[PDB]
Amino acid sequence: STNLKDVLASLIPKEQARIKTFRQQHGNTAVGQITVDMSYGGMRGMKGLIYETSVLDPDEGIRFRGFSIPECQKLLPKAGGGEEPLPEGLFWLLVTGQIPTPEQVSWVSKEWAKRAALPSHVVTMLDNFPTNLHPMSQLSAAITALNSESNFARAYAEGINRTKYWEFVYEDAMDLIAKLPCVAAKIYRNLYRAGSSIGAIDSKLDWSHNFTNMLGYTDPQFTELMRLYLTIHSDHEGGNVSAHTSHLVGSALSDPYLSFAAAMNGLAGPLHGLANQEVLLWLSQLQKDLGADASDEKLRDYIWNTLNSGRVVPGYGHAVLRKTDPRYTCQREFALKHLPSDPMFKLVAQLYKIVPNVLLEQGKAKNPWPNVDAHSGVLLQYYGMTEMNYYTVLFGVSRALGVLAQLIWSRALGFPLERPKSMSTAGLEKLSAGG
Amino acid sequence: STNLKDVLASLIPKEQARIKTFRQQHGNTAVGQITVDMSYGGMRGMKGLIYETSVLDPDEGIRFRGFSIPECQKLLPKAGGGEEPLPEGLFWLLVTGQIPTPEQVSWVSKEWAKRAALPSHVVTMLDNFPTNLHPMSQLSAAITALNSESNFARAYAEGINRTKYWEFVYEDAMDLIAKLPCVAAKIYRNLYRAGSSIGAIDSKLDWSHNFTNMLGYTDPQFTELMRLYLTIHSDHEGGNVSAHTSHLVGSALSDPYLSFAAAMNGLAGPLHGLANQEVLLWLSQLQKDLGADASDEKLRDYIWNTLNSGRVVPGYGHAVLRKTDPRYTCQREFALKHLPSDPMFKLVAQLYKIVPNVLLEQGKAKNPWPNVDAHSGVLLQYYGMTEMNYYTVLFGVSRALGVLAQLIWSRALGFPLERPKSMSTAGLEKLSAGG
Ligand SMILES: CC(C)(COP(=O)(O)OP(=O)(O)OC[C@H]1O[C@@H](n2cnc3c(N)ncnc32)[C@H](O)[C@@H]1OP(=O)(O)O)[C@@H](O)C(=O)NCCC(=O)NCC[C@@H](F)C(N)=O
Ligand SMILES: CC(C)(COP(=O)(O)OP(=O)(O)OC[C@H]1O[C@@H](n2cnc3c(N)ncnc32)[C@H](O)[C@@H]1OP(=O)(O)O)[C@@H](O)C(=O)NCCC(=O)NCC[C@@H](F)C(N)=O
Ligand SMILES: O=C([O-])CC(=O)C(=O)O
Ligand SMILES: O=C([O-])CC(=O)C(=O)O
């Protein structure tokens, strides 16, 4: 009775028509200007893509189809006896723009359990990888290796009419989301619980729950942490590295597997998703240098040393946000309720009072406030997941949700190849006169 | 005596200063405007990146550091007794902006031979991949898997000051370029010459030549074809999918291996580099449907069928070019001189007279002229490399040259995170009023 595919089939045509007419009336309307500095500056401040699933406000933070995080916490279906929103429902909301019912949500859950299966070549590959190969690298390679199963790649090669692309993107999106956790978990076990198995998927549990079982975690609060984690890391508008990467690559008709794997390569950058891991490594050195209960003056000292050494303070600053990230806050709130006395937490808490000030003092960062990465590993560490090099993988798993949600839309709406014009410094100097 | 690293060390500071002052004077100068339609249209027509290595003219075609293809053919060092430009020299030109000497060129050649070596984990991986896994997929996975050797990743993790990034990017760029051919060739042999070995690198040959030997080709004209192939496919300004992908991903500090592998995922799209393979598959069906010597009326018919079926005619059209691609011409010229009587060539030739007209007639394509992909496989087929699914790999190998050339520059000049602002249809309608 529930079928997202049928829902989308009705939704698509209405949106097509709506954009059609809009463009008819305003396609030539200018929404902005490009300056030299924006070009030199990684397009900062440039309105350059259409991304439907979420929109980030520099002051207010992210909105998913119009709903802020608190709204989601409050409207999205939760697990039986749960408090955290199920990621399944977030997906539904991104995809349809509507809040789902719990019945709808459980359908996603069954769908994802039904579709989870790995081909032997991928299993073999993971099991043969060396332990010194980074988790994100093993993840990306494995997703790329899964493209032999692409339904989209196969229909394209069969000559499918372009109007049906979305249909195949949809299938691969659902299959990929379903497989992610098994891939991710196999890496965790091969690297950290060598000789053990991830086991089987229980068609009866939610996605997060099957994930945590494959990861080998029993604590129920952990399961709750996971549901939240996976929901809040899902999407962050379209201009962020990982999302933009998936967009750009999918724009050339590369299948979802390939687009996703490229995005992961983007997420693995220190200035992007890798910050989650970097925050923890930074804290570890901290506590190692100074030792567990530091003084504010010593924290300042340690911050300055990093800055003076031509390095960044991980988990602070943002390309678009201008205030403290609601994702950070949302994590703080969870810590306060569940592990208020953790020393690491306490350390993170203390940094909140110091870091922004130092940054302000330094005078370079546009946004001195923390971002989501400043607070995530601390929560994970608490429950026993101390492998910091694996943290980004979790972020990867979550991000699939948003990026793949949009991906279907991009193909449904017929977005073309992303191909902007480049310029050389010399060509640009000429264009103007030069300086 | 020759050391590109030392040359760059002198070059870098001058460029820094030059951009500095320019920006001082014109950073706020507007170079363009953004309209609704550009946003909806994959940034078509938007000046959005700074890319130093090459600049594409919509009428004239690509210029590499100011030199057109004919100029390169004419100025770049050639092999002993050769006629085709060595890719090594093209690299030097991209990187320094200066035409190299043959002595310089031979240094690149030795450097690339010295640095070529694959780690066992990567070898193992390739050898375990299934035959149904696409060549581009095996390539991308393998490059990602090589990041365990990244010098840049390692120095970043050690806390290197940001001013030294280029130095490590440089090393990885050279190591990666050196390894590409071995990777590429191992895939070719595992897939198509099962049981044989790629052999060893001869520190005495040029890069293209060691490549063709590992591929198992003896014809000297083939070697010449390769040198040309690899030179002309090298770079195509910064807004193309693969280049932009590498740029965006490297912008987050992901290492060159990861940035390159993501670019490859971009290249593997049907609307991008995969067209080379698609052209051949299209021709094969053609000749199969119609049979070897077709009539113009039947060629038209066949073109129309494709178009009417919601498909693209591979190898025709371009996002920026408005006239026939000089890369196409350059290939035609080679065919005319070396395999003028090939039936396939002849077919390609015949299409040149028909395709653009049909396209013009259809009224959709902005550019009805052929692009580089319309002419490449035909040349390869002639020499015995009939595995069409492998063609994109060659394009991949070549592209490393341009993208990695720029990559060093991006980090030398301190380009920041690429992060434009996205918008939703609803947010945009509001911004205006809506249509
Ligand atoms: C996220 C970030 C790359 C945004 O960059 P951008 O919009 O260019 O930042 P900006 O305009 O404030 O930069 C102004 C100056 O302040 C510097 N600065 C910014 N954030 C800084 C930080 N956390 N520590 C030190 N210096 C910093 C920045 O590097 C720049 O210096 P240069 O002039 O020499 O280029 C940046 O604030 C940063 O480097 N953060 C540290 C890494 C991090 O936390 N990454 C995870 C981000 C998270 F949202 C995610 N998962 O994507
Ligand atoms: C390269 C290309 C994606 C540029 O796209 P774009 O700048 O959006 O093209 P455009 O502005 O002319 O498109 C106008 C219309 O003509 C259509 N059209 C363009 N080229 C076409 C072709 N070769 N066959 C059929 N229809 C085509 C295009 O799809 C579009 O239709 P919609 O309105 O329904 O979107 C495009 O011309 C194309 O689809 N080419 C066929 C694939 C190909 O040859 N790829 C290799 C390109 C090569 F340069 C490379 N290696 O990257
Ligand atoms: O929005 C961005 O630029 C980075 C970020 O926080 C994310 O991708 O979650
Ligand atoms: O320039 C582009 O958009 C595509 C192209 O021909 C290339 O990347 O070689």
Image (cartoon, coloured by chain):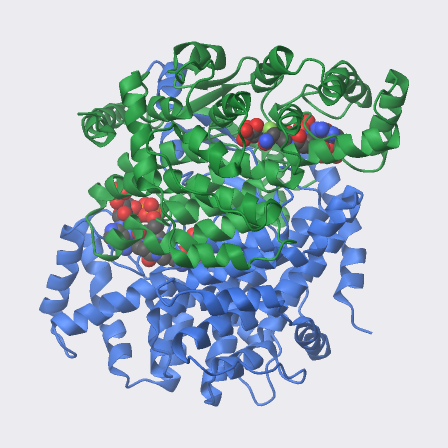
Chain colours: A blue, B green
Q: Can residue A59 be seen in this view?
A: no
Residue A89: percent from left, percent from top: 63, 72
Q: Can residue A158 be seen in this view?
A: yes
**Residue B100 lies in quadrant:** top left
Horizontal side, residue A355 vs residue A194: left or right: left
Horizontal side, residue A214 vs residue B101: left or right: right
Residue drawn at x 55%, y 45% is B189
Q: Nearer the viewer, residue A94 or A191?
A: A191
Image mark count: 0
Residue A37: percent from left, percent from top: 36, 32
Residue drawn at x 88%, y 28% is B290
The N terminus of chain A: image quadrant:
bottom right
Residue drawn at x 64%, y 84% is A202
Residue drawn at x 40%, y 47% is B257
**Residue B358 lies in quadrant:** top right
Horizontal side, residue A352 vs residue B291: left or right: left
Q: In this view, does A299 lie above or below A424?
A: below
Q: Which of A165 and B213 is in front in this view?
A: B213
Residue B368: percent from left, percent from top: 71, 20
The C terminus of chain A: image quadrant:
top left
Residue A61: percent from left, percent from top: 45, 59
**Residue B291 lies in quadrant:** top right
Q: In this view, does B136 lie above or below A422?
A: below
Q: Which of B434 and B142 is in front in this view?
A: B142
